[PDB]
Amino acid sequence: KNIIKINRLRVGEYFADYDPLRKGVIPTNKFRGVISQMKIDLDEEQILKLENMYILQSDPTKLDYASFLEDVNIVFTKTGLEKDPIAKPVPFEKKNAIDPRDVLTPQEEEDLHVLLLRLGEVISKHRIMFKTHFQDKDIAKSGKVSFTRFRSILDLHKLPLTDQQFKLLCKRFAHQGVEFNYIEFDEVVKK
Amino acid sequence: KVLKADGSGVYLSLYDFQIGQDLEFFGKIFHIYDCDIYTREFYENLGIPQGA
Amino acid sequence: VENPYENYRIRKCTLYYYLSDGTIHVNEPKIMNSGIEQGVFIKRQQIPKQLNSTDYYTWEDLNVGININLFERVFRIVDCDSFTKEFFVYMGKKMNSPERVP
Amino acid sequence: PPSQKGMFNPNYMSTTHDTYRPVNCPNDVTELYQPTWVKMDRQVLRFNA
Amino acid sequence: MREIVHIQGGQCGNQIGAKFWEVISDEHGIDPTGTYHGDSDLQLERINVYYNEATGGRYVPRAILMDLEPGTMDSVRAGPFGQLFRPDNFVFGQTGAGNNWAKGHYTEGAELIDSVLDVVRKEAEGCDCLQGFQITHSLGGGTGSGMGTLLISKVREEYPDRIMETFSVVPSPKVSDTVVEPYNATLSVHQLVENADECMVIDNEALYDICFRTLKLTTPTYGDLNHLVSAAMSGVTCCLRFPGQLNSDLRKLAVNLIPFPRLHFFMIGFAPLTSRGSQQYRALTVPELTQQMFDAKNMMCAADPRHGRYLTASALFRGRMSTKEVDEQMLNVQNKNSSYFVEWIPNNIKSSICDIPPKGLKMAVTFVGNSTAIQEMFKRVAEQFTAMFRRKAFLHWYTGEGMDEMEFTEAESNMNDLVSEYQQYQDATA
Amino acid sequence: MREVISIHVGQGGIQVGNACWELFCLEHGIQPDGQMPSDRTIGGGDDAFNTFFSETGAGKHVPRAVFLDLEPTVIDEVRTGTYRQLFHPEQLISGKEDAANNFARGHYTIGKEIVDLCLDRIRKLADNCTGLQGFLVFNSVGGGTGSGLGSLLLERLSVDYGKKSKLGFTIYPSPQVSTAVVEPYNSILSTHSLLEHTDVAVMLDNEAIYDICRRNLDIERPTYTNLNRLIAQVISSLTASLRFDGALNVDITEFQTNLVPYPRIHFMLSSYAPIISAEKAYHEQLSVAEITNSAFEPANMMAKCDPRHGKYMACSMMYRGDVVPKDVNASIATIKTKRTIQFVDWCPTGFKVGINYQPPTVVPGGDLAKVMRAVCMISNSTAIAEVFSRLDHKFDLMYAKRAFVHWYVGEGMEEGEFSEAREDLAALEKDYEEVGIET
Amino acid sequence: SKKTILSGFMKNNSIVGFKECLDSQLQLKDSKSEYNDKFQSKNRIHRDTSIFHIRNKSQII
Ligand SMILES: Nc1nc2c(ncn2[C@@H]2O[C@H](COP(=O)(O)OP(=O)(O)OP(=O)(O)O)[C@@H](O)[C@H]2O)c(=O)[nH]1
Ligand SMILES: Nc1nc2c(ncn2[C@@H]2O[C@H](COP(=O)(O)OP(=O)(O)O)[C@@H](O)[C@H]2O)c(=O)[nH]1
Ligand SMILES: [Mg+2]
């Protein structure tokens, strides 16, 4: 849903050509091909979990896509029904996917607040600006490289930290597993 | 239809087929070891189950 | 679907009911730079409660702040004319508190 | 699953139905007779040897 | 596949087409909001024959509403199922023809028709594989009978291989609502005979007679007449949309019904038609259906079939029935009524079966019979035309628009030539 | 290692192919999805299905057939039916626009863009086989696309393959019952086309089969499916000798060498016996003598022709079940003894007989019952001239005034094409008359 | 209050004899067609051979 939301992909047409008799059911292999062709990344477990109950109970060949289209198109607009004036659709902003990896499940976030305060105080006293080195290090201008080069910049400006608080900070601010973005880091150390 | 090999002059029937038991068809000895699912169900219905 | 500014549009219209022969007329007024071909919505005719039936609407089935079905479109009556208000109290039929059209 | 035949009203019984009752049978046969070979059609056992 | 587009002309044409589209939408389970709510899987297999799919999942007919006055289309829009039509397909002028065929064919229509030709070209090129066009118009009204026939001429000139059927309502003497009917009727027939691939004639007089005698209802109305016409229209092309034992579409019907290229005027009827109180007591069978089909009073025309001989006849059955019974019934009819059937073509009746009955009926039949009895219509129309034309009455209203009397004389001569050569095959023998 | 390919063109061909293929699948034990069940086998032996099917390597089986039409309705119905998984998706060839009962349309205009795909599919199917016996083709002869596409297909196959045998099972219009009005025209044209291209042709008009259903099966309102089931039973009884062991087997090539006295005369009419319902099938013994008497009975011919109006040239009869050769000999002796049946003098012995051990199979929900014995008859007789004469009369009645001629002329056909077919039919009549006279 | 209610707008926009057909004539499902009664049944490898002969005169239809 989020990928269709942000990339603005209309999956309606690419299913119609494979169901010329308006039956609303297409073979599973063609479903896999068309869903992979639409540039959205696919995982073996993700493909199997998309098979789930969208397959018909009669043999592993047929798959009904009308329900899938209804479920994925609800985000753009509630165009399915117009004959209820009280019901109102919801303007859309990106729903972040909830997952244990991106959340600090244990409660130690209070010391993260203390570290943020300490960094803010020291950067205010020393009036150090270091976004330029971050934006210089990367070349895609999207997200900074992993922490092994991130510590180099944090040590270049005289402000190093021990293993514990660095581990907490990098765990908090890491994304996708190995990459360590920086723009949100600067927005967090905000004045 | 095949006559019994013992020379009694009687045709073979359903009760002459048993898993692990030999037969005789024209000077040969056949040993049967397995049968399909349907045959197993049919024999159980009569009351003469086949062997493992 | 494809309008960048909007996702849902609200069309407003006025409903006229005639006591002479129990017929209903509905039209929507014009809006300047509306970009919509706007005019008469339903001719002066008797409208059955359900499609393809012979059970028509009467004045006792009309009220403010209620949903009404007109050819499988569900209108929501928000307010009524001032003159209509004396009619219901003259006939003795209780009316509801009107809301505003969002 | 035999047919109903539960409506067998005596008040409307014809004379020749009342006389020629089913003799030498427990009851009235309803199943149409068919030979053995049509009943055991396409019935084959299989063994591995 | 093999879809057809729809073009409507005149007030009568728009009134007919509105009920036709309501009937079709009810048959296919499309609500007037354009949202499918059917129950049978066969309701959506061949919907592309008449409909286009738009983003958002609603269905829009491929119909074009063309006229010389905005009032009647503003009225038909406000009716039920009137929101289906795309607002871009509405094309209209502001002046009007005023029941003047010359004005509607030379002055105003010739100037206006470029836009409607553009939209027709767009609709025809949009489809995957065009099958044909179908037109509904009246031959008594100026703007319809003129602008529509010029449109037919241009469409035929642009698409020489496709099929062109027109449902035409001709003026009757008993029921007349216009003083200048014969003039534009003759002028319309002149152009229609040369261009139209198929033509089906309907009379308000015959519709009233049917509504008064068969249905036995006290107050016939234009709604009921349009309902008759719409059911008859849908019966012809039902077999193109639904599976049948014997498939037969419009091209097959034309090939099997038209003996010679200039004889393409057919007269139609529908069965069963029963009164409200007598619906529970009648039984629907093939013999009953075929007897009510071949009943003379059930025809939708003032032409009386027993004053002439049938050239060919066609019946389109709907429902589940046996082909043996159907064929024996048609053979029995042909054998018992051998005097009314032309003899130098053997077994001159065509049959077809479609397994999907009309909505609400166990069985139904549509009849299309090419009979030689229609010449009386043309004879009476020409009689009135020449009676009015020997004195040049109302002639200046046509001659002031660049048209002369030579065209009137040519139209009359061609009309009489059609009548004569059409009667020739009635008396021709082997 | 013996194979045969069946070609179904036109609505009638497709609708009879449905029945024959469901019958074949039921007879060979293949489920509608195409997979033989893992358990619950119904028949012994191997490669019995190899005549009509081809093993995919692992699992299912594929028919050796191709479906043609210029209208998508029937093909879509087949592709939506329960047999969707059986046929290969690229042999249900469908067009866009129909011929609309026009032989010129189906032969000159819109069939030339589909015959290429059809022939490519035929080549692909024929490459798989190794001992190809011949081709079977089904087509209603009074229909535009059927007639035209059959003409084109056989014309191409006669030169691409040559000596390979082709069998055509046509459905001629009834003497007085018909559904169209121009069918004599394209019937004459297609008879012209297939006379010089077909090895064996069978007359299977509908009125006689209607009468058979009314009399024997006791059905007053039959549909086309019963007729198709009877035709399918005829096909199965005809082809059972290729895939089932018998006392006297007969191949496809054993027909042209025994039933065709002269290359021109290869039109035959079929008879089948017994046709009987379950309500009365078990009250009589159904002996071979009585079933062959029923087969020779004139009112049971599947074509509306009277064998009593002409002499017999030769006869072909195939028995399946538990029939005995001495019973067959006695029955043939009695038939020869009978006086109302007469053969030509220059054919002293006029019977070719076949015996098969596999009894006919029964389709659930059908009309026929289960019998131990059955006989199918293919006979060549001089009586077949009357149908040609009556269609010639009907053709002349309409061609006197040049009715409907423009609808064929406008699609590339020359004006004189009708005439040559006309004298070809007249010459066929004269050939029958010349052969039938005594010496 | 029997015929005094009539008005032009109400009268001309009401169908009298072409409304819904009375029931007991609607009893056909539009979903079912030919080739679906018999070739869409299911088909069985082993059939049921039981046939019953009742002592009731068959109804004529
Ligand atoms: N035996 C039999 N004949 C049929 C059947 N259906 C149609 N016919 C015959 O076919 C003739 C007309 O041809 P169609 O089957 O309708 O179709 P076609 O031959 O492919 O020609 P087109 O209609 O142009 O597609 C009719 O005169 C019928 O006699 C059927 O189911 N069984
Ligand atoms: N069936 C039917 N005929 C109508 C209707 N309204 C008008 N007519 C006929 O149409 C004729 C008038 O044609 P007209 O509408 O003026 O044609 P136009 O000039 O093209 O709009 C009259 O003689 C009527 O008989 C209607 O609602 N239904
Ligand atoms: Mg056809």
Image (cartoon, rainbow, N blue to C red):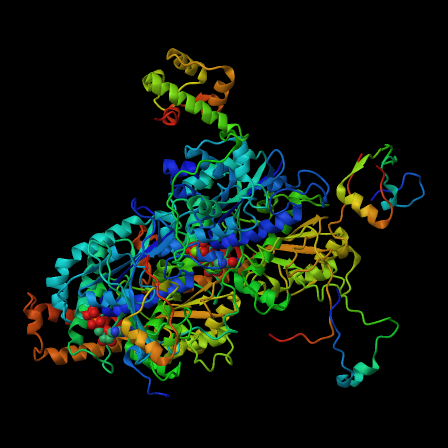
Q: Residue at x 42, y 43 (%)?
A: F115
Q: Quarter of the image for the N terminus of chain F: give it.
A: top right
In the image, residue C62 lies at what x, y percent?
A: 37, 72
Q: Nearer the viewer, residue C6 or F107?
A: C6
Which quadrant holds the C terminus of chain F? bottom right
Quadrant of the image occupied by residue E368: bottom left
Residue E399 in the image: above or below residue F100 = below
Whether residue F188 is visible, yes or no, is no
Is residue E182 positioned above or below A75 on the image? below
- As drawn, is A139 to the left or to the right of E292? left
Q: Is residue C102 visible?
A: yes
Between E96 and F216, the one nearer to me in the picture: E96
User: Residue, x 58% and y 70% (percent of image)?
Assistant: F220
Q: Position of residue B3 (x, y in %)?
A: 87, 42
Residue sitting at x 24%, y 81%: E175
Residue E286 position within the rendered picture, expressed as x and y whole percent measured from the top left = 49, 73
- Decide if residue F16 is on the left or right side of residue C98: right
Whole-percent x and y of residue F222? 57, 65
Q: Nearer the viewer, residue F294 or B6?
A: B6
**Left or right placement of residue B14 versus residue E224 in this view:** right
Picture residue at 37% right of the left edge, 88% below the top: G2
User: From what the image shows, is residue F360 above or below residue D8?
Assistant: above
